[PDB]
Image (cartoon, rainbow, N blue to C red):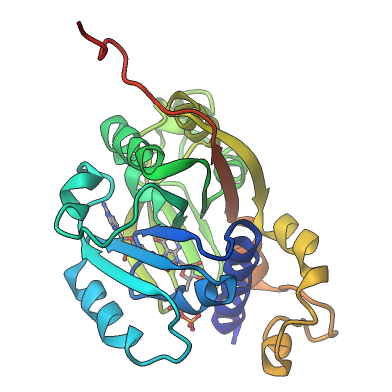
Length: 295
Ligand SMILES: Nc1nc2c(ncn2[C@@H]2O[C@H](COP(=O)(O)OP(=O)(O)OP(=O)(O)O)[C@@H](O)[C@H]2O)c(=O)[nH]1
Ligand SMILES: Nc1ncnc2c1ncn2[C@@H]1O[C@H](C[C@@H](N)CC[C@H](N)C(=O)O)[C@@H](O)[C@H]1O
């Protein structure tokens, strides 16, 4: 099953990412945490506290009722319904004094692209991330690669109204063709909508492009310096050497091609390894808002 291979691969990527930046005793803030898909991964890292926030009350309840159903829970868990992009994060976390801010890690797995709906939303999300971190703390995540998206968008003539591409397990469909009509450049960093379909996961839901240059430039304004940016395919090849020993025999088989080498082939190759990038930033400065220091 191709979609299974993709799920396996994307979980391997998340392990590689989490265990690279997260250290024993860390406090972790997972924005857009969904249904607690990444709890086991933070366990291996040896964290102290996990703080999950998601806008969907349904998802948080499935997260609560599921943490109980696992062994080796050596860490405190706080799960919160809240909007991490549209609203200040202090709104969401004030009712939860247990939370130990500032924290060591902020993670956004497959969600930061919902924040690029508007400039206002993108700036709050990043200010939320920056406000939350110790200096020396890391913000890491996974988003669609704007460079892969540009590569594909560049291949369409101006005639095509709603540019679309995909394969058997995924499809992207752009709202308009303003990119092509604007000499193969976005009119704006924000609000660049496309509909994403992934087999048995996302059902034609609107997302936004994240021009990596804009993410990097906003992060800098708020005191985050980029320390790594790699597409999944390149990230995996770099990290896989130190993971083969740690994979269980069944985990090994789910990450192997039919020839026995490690990786993805076929439709998964594009849908998983080319379409997504990881990133990691380090907080280097404490942000102070312009014109905010008064007598
Ligand atoms: N573009 C995009 N992809 C997403 C988003 N959310 C999830 N995905 C992708 O959906 C894939 C599969 O999601 P699910 O099938 O729900 O994965 P899961 O709950 O971890 O399931 P198992 O891996 O089987 O335990 C992930 O590996 C991501 O690549 C999103 O908001 N945007
Ligand atoms: N403004 C928002 N604030 C918080 N969560 C949001 C917001 N917008 C979307 N989300 C959530 O982001 C999640 C996106 C999921 N694709 C990711 C879940 C999980 N992190 C994973 O690795 O799959 C969903 O659970 C959404 O409800």
